[PDB]
Image (cartoon, coloured by chain):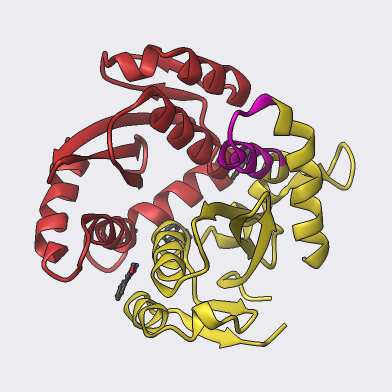
Chain colours: A red, B yellow
């Protein structure tokens, strides 16, 4: 469970949002990139893997994920590759704040901040951020 | 050191800028190549970082990029207190060593920096019974 992520793209305003969801926690990382390239994908994956303990990524069938640069990055970083609730949610927060910023990429990271900090449930609840650190700390 | 305290520093290599955030208690790092130390680039780095880990305070070098109104606006929004000029120099030293060990596997410097971040955060310190910066940050931050 703790090493598993799902990666998805979302299309808005002529660019691509790459979104990686930590499956057990709902925690997200996201980045706006100009186009969905093998290179951009590979880079997003190395960044994520130096930050969190990434064992497996679950992706769509896209040609970006089967590129030699993506395969080189996965081999080096130790990532096995394979083939919405949190993601429609992200798109909705983007809308709730998109107004508040000049560029989309600013509203996107504002949305990540909001998602990852938000307590789910009542008093006794946890944010997605809290849940991922607890999951990984427990594992260790 | 609080679990919420970060130190930001910059390094220049090959004519490019590397912004580095160090989690002071653990030695964990986040780093990115940016085009130039502008307010808008520094603000965006901080917004990203604060969205990923619980950032309470940032100690900075008091560079002109931090005096930017946009950086203050970002810290305010994210609930970060900015402490300028308030003192890991062997960190910017450390990252450049590791960047040299991987530089030949990467066509572009920015890729080599993420590779170095990865090696840094996974490295066991203190010998075979020790722990990585990555292990230490989650242990320090975990509330339950
Ligand atoms: O369980 C400890 C904890 C984790 C966080 C956190 C908040 C936001 C992003 C990542 C982690 O806050 N408290
Ligand atoms: O200019 C890029 C940018 C701006 C911000 C910002 C975030 C929150 C409030 C105000 C400004 O973050 N990155
Ligand atoms: O040893 C398991 C483990 C790995 C990590 C980690 C966290 C952040 C970056 C790199 C590694 O945390 N717990």
Residue under the point 53% across and 21% down: A74
- Residue A2 showing in the rendered view: no
Q: Residue A105's x, y, as percent?
A: 27, 55
Assign the magenta stretch its main secondary structure: helix
Which contiguous range is marked in magenta? Answer: B105-119
Q: Is residue B140 above or below residue A54?
A: below
Residue under the point 51% across and 63% down: B36
Is B110 part of what is drawn in magenta? Answer: yes
For ligand 3, which image quadrant applies?
Answer: top right
Which is nearer the eye, B45 or B26? B45
Q: Residue A138's x, y, as percent?
A: 56, 44
Which is nearer the eye, B72 or B3? B72
Residue under the point 15% across and 65% down: A97
Q: Is residue A107 above or below residue B86?
A: above
Q: Quadrant of the N terminus of chain B?
A: bottom right
Number of callouts:
0
């Amino acid at each position: 469970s703790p090493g598993i992520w799902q990666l998805d793209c979302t299309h808005l305003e002529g660019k691509v949002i790459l979104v990686a969801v930590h499956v057990a926690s709902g925690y997200i990382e996201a980045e706006v990139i100009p186009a969905e390239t093998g290179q951009e994908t590979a880079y997003f994956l190395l960044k994520l893997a130096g930050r969190w303990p990434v064992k497996t990524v679950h992706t769509d069938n896209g040609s970006n994920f089967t590129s030699t640069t993506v395969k080189a990055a996965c081999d080096w970083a130790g990532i096995k590759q394979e083939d919405e609730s949190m993601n429609k949610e992200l798109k909705k927060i983007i809308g709730q704040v998109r107004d508040q910023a000049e560029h989309l990429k600013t509203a996107v990271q504002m949305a990540v901040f909001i998602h990852n900090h938000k307590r789910k449930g009542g008093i006794g609840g946890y944010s997605a951020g809290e849940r991922i650190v607890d999951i990984i700390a427990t594992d260790i």
